[PDB]
Every structure is written in structure tokens, then in C-alpha cells.
Image (spheres, grey):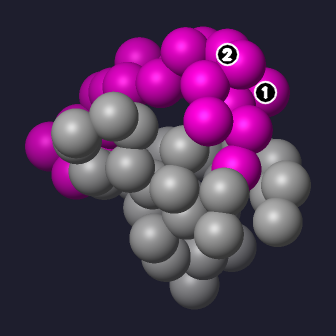
Amino acid sequence: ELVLALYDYQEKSPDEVTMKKGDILTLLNSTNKDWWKVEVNDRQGFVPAAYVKKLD
């Protein structure tokens, strides 16, 4: 399942990942209402669910 970064997000903790607006990410875990685990290129970690949008 693919998602679109709606906004830039810079990582602020060791479970997080940095993404840039318009980036296309792989949705890994949408279990948490607030933080979704995504893959941005080679790196995986959590971003705000609200800053990404399911395409798929």
C-alpha cells in the first residue's frame, strides 16, 4: 500500500523517519491512529499519519 507525503516531516526521535512533501512512501503499519510506519527510499520508521494520504 502506497501513501503520499502531504508535508515535509523531519524526524524527532529514534523511531521516526524524515520525509519530504510529494514523496511516495510504502505504508508498513497503519495500526496507530497517530503515527504510521512508512518506508522512505531505503529507511523505515514512523511519521504522522495525518501528514500522509493513502493512494491505494
Q: Is residue 51 visible?
A: no
Most extreme residue toward the left, as rendered? 14
Q: Position of residue 10 (x, y in %)?
A: 41, 18
Q: Which residue is mark 1?
A: 6
Q: Position of residue 8 (x, y in %)?
A: 60, 15
What residue is drawn where x is 81% and y is 58%?
A: 54
25, 45: nearer the viewer: 25
47, 2: nearer the viewer: 2
Q: Is residue 10 magenta?
A: yes
What residue is drawn where x is 55% and y is 15%?
A: 20
Q: Residues within 10 Å of mark 2 (few under 14, many from 20)?
A: few
Q: Is residue 41 above or below residue 22?
A: below
Q: Position of residue 53 (x, y in %)?
A: 82, 48
Q: Which residue is mark 2?
A: 21
Q: Is residue 50 above or below residue 32?
A: above
Place residue 28 in its image quadrant: bottom left
Magenta span of residues = 3-24
Q: Amino acid at mark 1?
A: Leu
Q: Is residue 12 magenta?
A: yes
If you read the primary sequence from the N terminus, does the residue marked by circle 1 or circle 2 appear first? 1
Q: Is residue 4 left or right of residue 1?
A: right
Q: Are marks 1 and 2 in contact (CB under 8 Å)?
A: yes
Q: Is residue 10 left or right of residue 34?
A: left
Place residue 6 in its image quadrant: top right
